[PDB]
Amino acid sequence: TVLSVGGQVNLLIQQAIDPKNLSRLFPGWKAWV
Image (cartoon, rainbow, N blue to C red):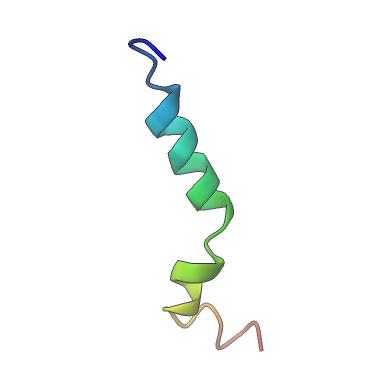
């Protein structure tokens, strides 16, 4: 940890790798049925 931004950038990749939650809050699931 030091001037390392890979912390927020990496974080953004993980959430983006598990959009099952946000997707559930959007029509994204009306097709996953």
